Image (cartoon, rainbow over all chains, first blue to last red; front, top):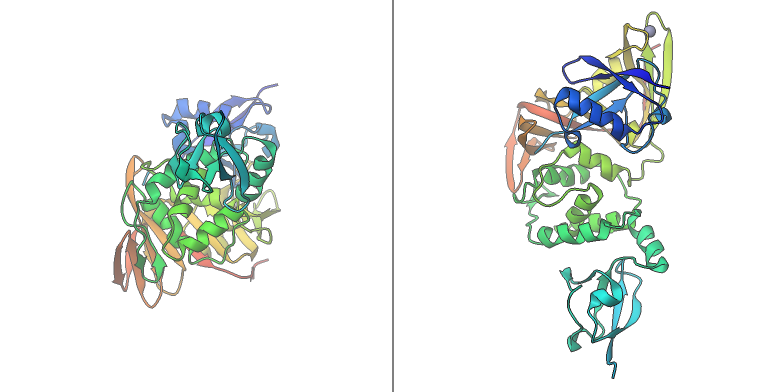
Length: 77
Length: 315
Ligand SMILES: [Zn+2]
């Protein structure tokens, strides 16, 4: 039952990702990682300000078709 | 033929358990991974001097399991093992008093941990996990070895790893007492009317987007699901503090407008944190180093603000 959501990077651009609401957030992060070049540990996703914990299904966050997840980069200090 | 000694085993340093230890078997064969004053003794057979000593063990059976859960509020099997590994190194750190607060002298890339400990000491927060609360009380007295090792254990970080201050705060605030924290946001789209969302807990005190608290109160430009761009603004806030974050940009900190802040020099592959608090003047705390200044304008990434209750004047 796949749908499409948007993931916006830190430059303000949103790529489309094909997902099922039963797949985990960790699954989605491996797609964003392959597209934007960052590896999973160095960024984290949010939806309407709420962070997404990796091993929970996407449907628990109320993701709709063409919703916008945000990509935030983790500093290394 | 069997010869034993009497010891105490524990997982929370409060509930002691009497144990008869066969001297012919290692502590590992009988209890699993075992520690004595932090020193790993899993492979060591009992010594006569171990009589009556207290040993740290991992919660192997059911009684220890619930005891460990009441103390640490985690079920991660590997938590106590990772806590002990970080504690080996954090005991060697120095925690000098700087500007009235306990800091951490530079070592093992602990500048992000230094900013966490400093920011915590200026916030009215309590920890629901008893292990975090006891270690925090010792931390304010210059004895922060346990607290730092716990922070690394809850964050799944090891000694020497580069770290993110806000991420680290997020892990620890899950165990904070933010039950009464309430935040109400309005999303005003000129097409799709108005929308209200209430946030609670850690989501009510943290925000990612701008460093300015006033920006949140007057209006933040947010995408709209319909296609436009709407404006998000704060309606009601009930908490002892708020934490504004943003990608490291250059920012002017004024006295009397904020509680404390963190700045970040470098890029997303390697950087350095220093902490800025506001007392009589702007204090900059870089590990063991203190620097006073009237003005500050640098690459800020986290800003904290004191708070009790705020109601918007907008409608
Ligand atoms: Zn709209």
